[PDB]
Length: 255
Length: 255
Ligand SMILES: [Cl-]
Ligand SMILES: [Cl-]
Ligand SMILES: [Cl-]
Image 1 (cartoon, rainbow over the protein chains, first blue to last red):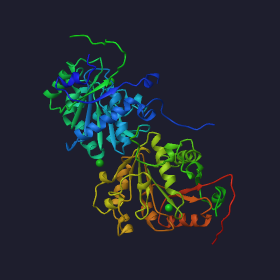
Image 2: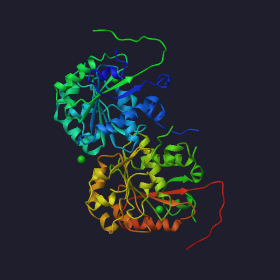
Image 3: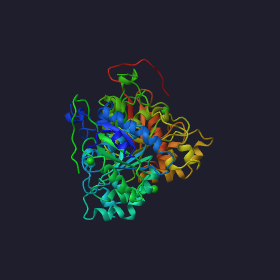
Image 4: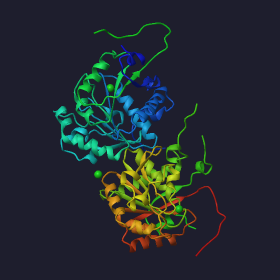
């Protein structure tokens, strides 16, 4: 188990941000509206988890200085890292700054951001890459967050083959000229190569490891493998960080 | 003066909405550190306000009117100066954006638009710079954080306002925009002040005229719709804005 920012620095891994977990988020005469609860970034802006994401923004602001490419790929070591939380909150935070952001859910097998943004999943990433849908037909707007999104679409029979099609390249090149920041949420590296095939058309790449769940080893093993591939892995993010119990104990099995 | 909708229906002028005045804003209202970067924007501040509910109604009427008519450009002009045309269009922009819709707002009042001041965004690269061929499209499209929609400001006042609107990039812009946004709102200078609305109106698919409660007369309004007619511009109707119930009067004027 990780649990400590410096517990990564020692491995040489640079941590762009440490994000604590929100407890309020676990608690979770006509007029007509839409969408459902809950989106932390807009609901509780003062939240401690959100304030940290802003610090994540300030970090990328520098980091992402003169790289020409404005596509930032977010991925995790393994499943349940809270990477979708980090990425979606980052999108909201950056957009809120008067910035044009495009969020794409590249987890063609298990992306669920359509549920989080309470948006349709009929036309998404898979339909486009397969050639069924034109680009403008798969880009929708997440009202509550104030940014544009592309859901995963209907789970395809050939996830990986689709990610390698030329259309993924056309999309990122196109997207890079129309948005100030393009966030790509991808499957964990320790689960599929997908992040390596897409991480190769991106300027930045941040791996998100969860406090306690991830062993500082795999976060290096993940970055290492993305390095074998042309992927330009910058640092890492420590998500989950939960503290103050006045004792001495945690969790993390040893392999 | 003029107060209806009935007084408007009379001259055949079809009224899509009646927006009451907002006392909550008349006062300007105002219900650590690191603050925002804007000013009071009713649509997101007091959402349940009666002026915003009126706009929602406008949305509904516009939805039926803009029923399978394909062209998604909506031009909102006024009969005369200070008719509240910007409060109306900016509010509608926000409302429609919140329904998970990609919207583009453009200030086509190259001489007195102030929407950049309202959205408190930059005004160095705007419509005028783009129309003159100086700037590029992606350069002039910015994002309004609070509202959640994309905007294009006027830019620096050009020496040849009208000549630029007849350009060619105006059309080129509008049709390009029509393919990347679900809704395109174009704010134009008062019809009885310049010919601009009629030159731009020839590329919009729908047009609305906003008349102010008490300041306008059922005369000048139908006169504007008429001269827009001569130019071959789809003027679907009008909007009564400012309506302040529970009151009286104390002015004077006529023609
Ligand atoms: Cl996840
Ligand atoms: Cl294009
Ligand atoms: Cl005006």
